[PDB]
Image (cartoon, rainbow, N blue to C red):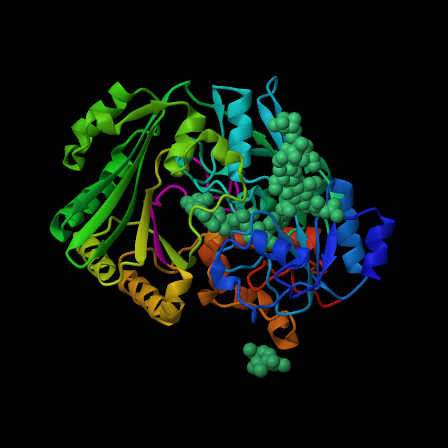
Amino acid sequence: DLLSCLTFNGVRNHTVFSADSDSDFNRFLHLSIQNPLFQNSLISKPSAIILPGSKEELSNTIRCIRKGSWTIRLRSGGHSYEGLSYTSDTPFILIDLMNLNRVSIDLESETAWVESGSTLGELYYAITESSSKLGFTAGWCPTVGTGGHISGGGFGMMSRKYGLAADNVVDAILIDANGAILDRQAMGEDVFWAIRGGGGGVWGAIYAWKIKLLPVPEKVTVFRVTKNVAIDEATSLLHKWQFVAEELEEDFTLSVLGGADEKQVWLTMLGFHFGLKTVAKSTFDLLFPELGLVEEDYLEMSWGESFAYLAGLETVSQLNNRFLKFDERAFKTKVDLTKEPLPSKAFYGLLERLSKEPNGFIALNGFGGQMSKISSDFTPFPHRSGTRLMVEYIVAWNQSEQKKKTEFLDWLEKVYEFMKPFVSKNPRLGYVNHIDLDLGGIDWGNKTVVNNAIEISRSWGESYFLSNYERLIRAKTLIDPNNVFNHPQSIPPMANFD
Ligand SMILES: *[C@@H]1O[C@H](CO)[C@@H](O[C@@H]2O[C@H](CO)[C@@H](O[C@@H]3O[C@H](CO)[C@@H](O)[C@H](O[C@H]4O[C@H](CO)[C@@H](O)[C@H](O)[C@@H]4O[C@H]4O[C@H](CO)[C@@H](O)[C@H](O)[C@@H]4O[C@H]4O[C@H](CO)[C@@H](O)[C@H](O)[C@@H]4O)[C@@H]3O)[C@H](O)[C@H]2NC(C)=O)[C@H](O)[C@H]1NC(C)=O
Ligand SMILES: *Cc1cc2c(c(*)c1C)N[C@]1(NC(=O)NC1=O)C(=O)N2C[C@H](O)[C@H](O)[C@H](O)COP(=O)(O)OP(=O)(O)OC[C@H]1O[C@@H](n2cnc3c(N)ncnc32)[C@H](O)[C@@H]1O
Ligand SMILES: *[C@@H]1O[C@H](CO)[C@@H](O)[C@H](O)[C@H]1NC(C)=O
């Protein structure tokens, strides 16, 4: 009996299923559903939601759930593009980690222990409060949870300088399928490697991450400038952008958000420099004068301020608000990684397609810099040297546009097909933090599929992990041979014939 088990172990914060919009259950379920695509009444719902308040409670929660037949779901920030932290085709218990959001900074070692329910914003805020000369490399969305994000890699505006969040993890506490509480020494190097990018919801429950804090200057420079242009100019800008993104030294990042509506194209240029505005502007004046940036576009501020600003927040304080919703639209997104430069026609066609669907947008990031200096097998994220760009295609809509859902999905499908020739091939590469079920999924309830799970899974597995897929399967067998942590695209354990 689950409830008696939780009570016996003093895991007191839990609620059982109820449809009442008023119920604490429904409120907690919806609190961290960060893609409204998955909020409706016909979606699968948990039989109970448990909010463990310590590593011991998390351990005992897993143990209690194991006594029954339920599927475990872990949720940190709830940002799964495919809602995989709070949906399941089989009855399930949702372990919501929002109360495990403590950040402990050690300024003597310049490291931090970060409970896995902490959001990126909570982490950034904690760091800024402790020091004006330390930061951390992770994504730009402040409400993303560290649990999912670091488990999948974690790319952001400082990745060209410092790599992924997962590339800067030096220890972690993993709670395994039997509730065992394991640090790096206890879990071993294969498992410690797998958790640093091998995907959330696969290895066990991360309780906390120990991260290395990273130097930042007291003043950095950023800009966020939207150019309103026509398609010919936008194409010229994007085509040159891909090279500048690369010719820039690691102390600079220039990224782009873009979209259109008939004749009008908008390109939002996001810039970050590890340094002062005189140097930042001089560099873009020389390398990319076509951007037409002026002195007033460049803002000098602290690292903490810069991360709040790039996210469009009003204040650094807002980083610490995990429930602040800046964009409450349902969305679907796909992503590509490139190995060869994109021809101008690829950007032209992308822009033409965006002009026909104003609810669509693209997000463009260059790799290079430190991303090319990290070996493909340092952590499970393999897209290092030779990888040029990450290109994201997004379509998003509010509730008033819900009837157009299929139209938006059609547009996104067509955009991804259009880009096929220009982007990585054999296989077409992906990124596990941009999990995409279009690639397929495992029905763990189907014996025939399960027998063939490894090779069925190679489709998306090689896309996300390339040559690292094999070691991930070895690590999965080590830490979760009974496949307690599973989802449609989780790494399968090795075939066993005992
Ligand atoms: C399972 O987990 C969930 C998720 O964590 C739990 O739900 C959370 O429960 C929290 C309470 O335990 C609740 O926090 C509350 O959040 C509200 C905002 O919605 C916040 O205003 C509350 O903060 C007040 O109360 C706490 C003590 O509970 C104080 O520490 C705090 O200082 C606040 O009191 C002050 O402000 C109040 C007005 O807001 C005044 O009425 C009060 O007098 C006091 O004012 C004095 O101090 C002020 C500051 O110096 C000063 O300005 C003033 O003049 C006075 O001197 C409270 O923290 C969360 O909202 C809730 N989270 C969610 C998602 O629902 C849940 O309880 C758990 N369930 C179980 C079974 O354990
Ligand atoms: C919603 C959103 C997502 C992203 C971005 C912004 C916004 C608003 N921006 C990103 N773009 C970038 O270039 N960099 C960004 O950060 C982006 O990539 N992005 C997607 C997120 O990074 C990922 O979706 C990330 O995995 C989400 O993390 P989180 O909020 O924790 O997501 P969850 O749905 O709770 O979990 C994801 C998977 O991981 C498992 N999991 C959660 N917590 C776990 C712990 N503690 N241990 C083990 N596994 C855990 C979940 O079960 C789920 O499978
Ligand atoms: C199991 O999977 C196989 C392969 O996808 C499929 O042919 C079959 O219909 C499935 N069986 C069940 C019980 O759904």
**Residue 109: x percent and y percent?**
61, 20
Q: In the shown orientation, is residue 105 left or right of residue 153?
A: right
**Along the line of sight, the residue nearer the viewer: 242 or 305:** 305
Magenta region: which residues? 372-396
Dividing the picture into quarters, in which one does residue 244 lie? top left
Which residue corresponds to the image point at 19% horizontal and 28% vertical from the top-left?
Answer: 294
Residue 400 position (above or below residue 265): below
The image quadrant in which ligand 3 is located: bottom right
Residue 20 position (above or below residue 143): below
**Residue 53: x percent and y percent?**
73, 42
> Do we see residue 28 in this rendering?
yes
- Image quadrant containing the N terminus: bottom right
**Residue 172: x percent and y percent?**
65, 37
Q: Is residue 376 magenta?
A: yes
Which residue corresponds to the image point at 39% horizontal and 68% vertical from the top-left?
Answer: 405
SS assignment for the magenta stretch, majority: loop
**Residue 56: x percent and y percent?**
78, 42
Residue 402 position (above or below residue 124): below
Q: Is residue 283 magenta?
A: no
**Along the line of sight, the residue nearer the viewer: 298 or 179:** 298
> Do we see residue 168 in this rendering?
no
Which residue corresponds to the image point at 31% horizontal and 29% vertical from the top-left?
Answer: 249
**Along the line of sight, the residue nearer the viewer: 440 or 35:** 35
